[PDB]
Image (cartoon, rainbow, N blue to C red; front, side, top):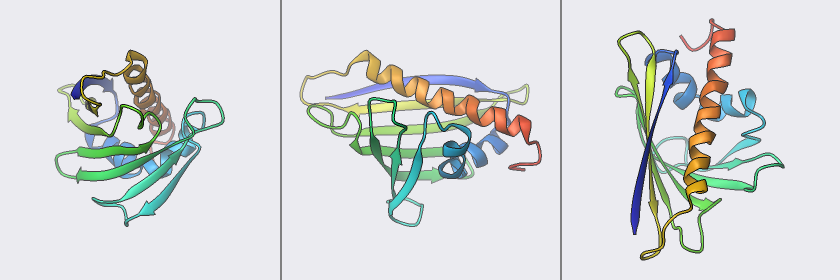
Length: 159
């Protein structure tokens, strides 16, 4: 079957700046500002646009070793990002792929909110463990606050 779960996290960083660092330059910032979350980001197939495959490895702590991600869509103007987890991690047994959509909306105060969306593809009527979804919510949130600390520490960046 197909299950969809949503989330929304706030950030002080304006959408314009957050996009460049969190999305446009994630594969170069995450392993730097969040080592206990991302160990290394390897490129497999593609230059970096739609159809690209990046091998994201995790530290020697998490239960997962790596995860293959496929770049689907990257809207630089509408601050939208779409990637799919095709291999590694939870993928297997009953789970096939994971369609993810990230959108950075600006707020009236000058901040921004992340409208993340997870769409899992299970086997027949098989469902997904709550902890699985709970993990991504923490995965992205930790990275978020990981990028905020840096941006606020280095104002002369991504601008």
